[PDB]
Amino acid sequence: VLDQYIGSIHSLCKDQHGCRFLQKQLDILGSKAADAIFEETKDYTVELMTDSFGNYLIQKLLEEVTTEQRIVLTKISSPHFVEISLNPHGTRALQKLIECIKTDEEAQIVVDSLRPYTVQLSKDLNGNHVIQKCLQRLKPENFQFIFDAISDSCIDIATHRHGCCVLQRCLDHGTTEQCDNLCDKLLALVDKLTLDPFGNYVVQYIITKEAEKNKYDYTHKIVHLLKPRAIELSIHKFGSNVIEKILKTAIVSEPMILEILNNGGETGIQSLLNDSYGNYVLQTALDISHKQNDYLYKRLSEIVAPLLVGPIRNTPHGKRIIGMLHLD
RNA sequence: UGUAUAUUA
Image 1 (cartoon, rainbow, N blue to C red):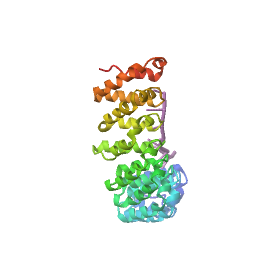
Image 2 (tube, rainbow, N blue to C red):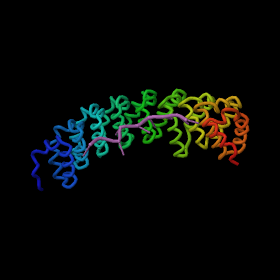
Image 3 (cartoon, chains in turn green, brown):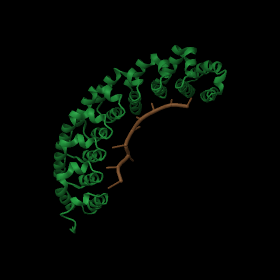
């Protein structure tokens, strides 16, 4: 019950060493010490949230505070979620707030506030992590808003440096109904997403998560749409990563290697040998077929061996493919 | 030989 600093808690926030202190205070006190710090600081929560040290207090304050006090802090901050979210410190406090909310009124207020700005926050360096925490902590019933918003600006988000990370959370935490809708849209531009600096990552993730669950739906729909362009995509900087992902995925592996032999032929396999990215594909196709199926490995092997003549033998990738020809 | 992802003191 020993407070010498009471009455002037707010001034202790000006310095890093002042905020660190208030937190040790909350750490050891910590109930009565919350009614205290709460009542003195509430009026500056959106200011403290976006501050270098305050925000840490706010984060301790949220763990320690009661429900009613959180609902007040939440009500006080909601008009300021956008500016809070685009902030490096603010994003941290707001994320914490979301981690701490227990009631539906709280989740209601938060989604209500964030709704109109989902796509915007989802393209933001600091903001996108607020959107991700909604996906990670809230009931699907609640974050339905995010899925709606993101499903509509689907390609915009999937092809964005940060947007693409939010899609990955959507796939992590959403309902089957929600993901299937998201994916149905994603699939409508699997071609363009595949060739994209960021979209290719989303394509790979759909495959990753199905392989995770051992239940395959869009993995097949992707492979169906893409496979006919196996070679063309194998020699693309980004698309080649998708092709390599398909190859490393056992339920679709053989068909795709078979696509290389079938419609690539000796020609397309030459292209792969000499290409900046294509050769990594060839290496993987060889590595995999080796492990998975000898007929395929042999058919591969006997086309490569004749083509591994000349200056190619001395190249970095040449040596690396040469070393993949007698593994049995 | 080839891609992203603030880990605020």
